[PDB]
Amino acid sequence: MTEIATTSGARSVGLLSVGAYRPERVVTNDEICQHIDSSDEWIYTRTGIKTRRFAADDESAASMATEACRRALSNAGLSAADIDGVIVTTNTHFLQTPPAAPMVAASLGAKGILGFDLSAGCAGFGYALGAAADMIRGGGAATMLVVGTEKLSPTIDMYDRGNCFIFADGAAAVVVGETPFQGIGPTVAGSDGEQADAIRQDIDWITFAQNPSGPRPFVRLEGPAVFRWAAFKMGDVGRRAMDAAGVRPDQIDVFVPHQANSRINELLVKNLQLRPDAVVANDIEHTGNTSAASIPLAMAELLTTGAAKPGDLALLIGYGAGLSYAAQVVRMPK
Amino acid sequence: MTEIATTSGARSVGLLSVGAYRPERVVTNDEICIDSSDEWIYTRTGIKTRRFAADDESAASMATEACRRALSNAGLSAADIDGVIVTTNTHFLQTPPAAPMVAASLGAKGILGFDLSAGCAGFGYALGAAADMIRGGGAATMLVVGTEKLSPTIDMYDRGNCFIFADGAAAVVVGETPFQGIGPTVAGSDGEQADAIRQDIDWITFAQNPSGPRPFVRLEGPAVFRWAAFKMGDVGRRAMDAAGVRPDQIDVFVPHQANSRINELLVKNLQLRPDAVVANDIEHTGNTSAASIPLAMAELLTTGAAKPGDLALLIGYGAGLSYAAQVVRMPK
Ligand SMILES: *SCCCCCCCCCCC(=O)O
Ligand SMILES: *SCCCCCCCCCCC(=O)O
Ligand SMILES: CCCCCCCCCCOC(=O)S
Ligand SMILES: CCCCCCCCCCOC(=O)S
């Protein structure tokens, strides 16, 4: 009797730019050997990390996202008024509400634009990019920001000899809009809810809030279990992502896995059967693991250093918390 | 150089089914006092009773229950679903996310998913994101579930809001339909009013100073009333417009169940048919935030007021100052 209208947008969409923010404070391996019993040698060998970035007390996941978003637009040659919507992916927004997106949009002077927060561990970016590209193609928006942002510092147990030296702070943003040629492939994603406990906050905020003066929550990590899972399962994931995009492994110029751990990633590369000269992102060396923020920060570093060029066929695999993953083939931004 | 494939899913996508979960325990107006009354609370809010989830229940647990039912009503098993989006404001864990757990609990542990946070516009956005993913080729059928557990967030001395919030979850199955079943998403926000609805103290600042006060949900009634009542009429007009439907065509208005008086003014402004049906689940459900709309859809469908395939305007509004709207067809 009646018909609901249907819309459509751009066919091809891509990473118009990347913009990275990294906090002033550089915390060395040595400067954590205080509260733990190990060396710089030890930490570096098992993780790949040399130094990491720590945000200041007044800095936040939303402030850092804003400064990243600000830089992204500059690199894309656009102002806030060109943006139709922003998606924030984070694990360290410390308010159940309000969301971060609207605050960010307002900070940048695009106060009324659409936006939500996407939470999916370190698969957030892959999912957010997916949703963005999907929204623009459907005609929901034309140009979008997607920003991985993280203030992990406050959640570290400085005595937790298993993960204290892994997490760090930062934010990086990309611009997604119409492009001459297809620049973002299909999103390949999934989960493993059974191993949800592998990466977690040990105490929920409500339990804690009812008994405040007792032990406070921290980020907890079952290393071995997350290693085995990432290293033995993401190899296939990436192949599903290349297969979807219709690309051979030997065509990937740039590998940007989530910066969880250097050993893991090394193993992922060998598995994926890439070219001997594919550029594998290793930002983790001086950035540390920045969760949902890692992939875009990885991209930015590879471009800043000139090891990757704009237009390079890249493969992104995000993996981590909740045991979730998201992957896709893209063209390098900027 | 080298091509990247351009894929495409099914063009037309709708709501196959709705499924609701509401906790056992009924908390009556009387069972909460501040300095108020049954006739006081019903006048400003439209609430009579609300439901509270038990101490062993969660956002995630209710979501699963809701999904499981949505799945039953769809005539589908968890193996038919390609992904789940959980929209919530009360999953009290920074990580891991709720979606894979719900996925695990449903018995489809492998499927994709995430948590989408956008105040009470969460559902509008999550529905949008779903249809978009299905139309794009990344999923054939999906669950969108709104879940909420606001009981522990409420401050019993807050004469402004303590009687407003409740617990509950409701999910929908989205998938290929003979005709277009989800209108174009119409959304936006007002960042400059982020504090209108907020958690007064962040979790870390609280954790670093536990001898101070604990966080609670704080609300600026007046500012939230002005905004919602006098802006969301336009949003409704923009959503009906995108859907290529006239106001006088709408069978069912389902605004977010924030406040009956807000929603009362909205209906007048929207200039719908005298016989348009208005979501009032709030009377006995209360404000369940990101879950209100699907709950209201299920309540209307259970009640007979809304039939399957009715034309329904959805308008989600709330925290962050975020809004999301669409014209959908009624499921089941
Ligand atoms: S993919 C990496 C996810 C782990 C970081 C998530 C944020 C910290 C976890 C919460 C810790 C806390 O604040 O208690
Ligand atoms: S759109 C509804 C806005 C209020 C619901 C958001 C969750 C409650 C805020 C958190 C309060 C707390 O810290 O417990
Ligand atoms: C002593 C070995 C070092 C631990 C290796 C496990 C690394 C997994 C960290 C992944 O966390 C995420 O952010 S995901
Ligand atoms: C000026 C009269 C005040 C009435 C109280 C307003 C209630 C606002 C409820 C907030 O809705 C949300 O879900 S947030």
Image: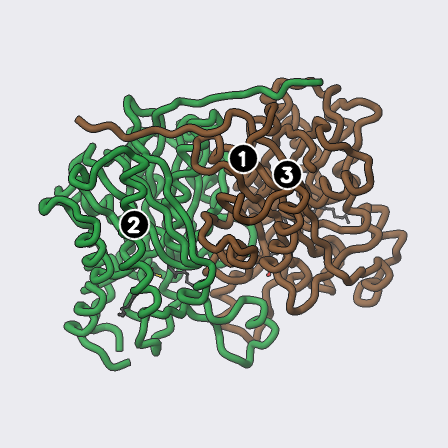
Chain colours: A brown, B green
Residue A182 occupies quadrant:
top right
Instruction: Tell me which image quadrant ligand 2 sits in.
Output: bottom left
Q: What residue is at 32 percent from the left and 69 percent from the top?
A: B221
In the depicted structure, whether residue A73 falls above or below residue B176: below
Residue B208 occupies quadrant:
bottom right
SS for dot 1: helix
Q: Do labels 2 and 1 share a chain?
A: no
* Residue corresponding to mark 3: A318
Q: Do labels 1 and 3 share a chain?
A: yes
SS for dot 2: helix
* Residue corresponding to mark 2: B234
| Lateral position of residue A35 relative to residue B319, left or right | right
- Is the residue under label 3 in contact with that under label 1 (CB below 8 Å)? no
Q: Residues within 10 Å of mark 3 (few under 14, many from 20)?
A: many
Residue A215 occupies quadrant:
bottom right
Going by the numbered disc 1, the residue's amino acid type is Gly
Q: Nearer the viewer, mark 2 or mark 1?
A: 2
The number of numbered badges drawn on the structure is: 3
* Residue corresponding to mark 1: A130
Q: Residues within 10 Å of mark 1 (few under 14, many from 20)?
A: many
Q: What residue is at 34 percent from the left and 54 percent from the top?
A: B317
- Chain at tag 1: A
In the depicted structure, whether residue A286 falls above or below residue B260: above
Going by the numbered disc 3, the residue's amino acid type is Gly
Q: What residue is at 35 percent from the left and 67 percent from the top?
A: B223
Going by the numbered disc 2, the residue's amino acid type is Asp
Across and down, in percent, residue B246 comes to 21, 37
Q: Which of marks 1 and 3 is nearer the N terminus?
A: 1
- Chain at tag 2: B
Q: What residue is at 20 percent from the left and 50 percent from the top?
A: B279
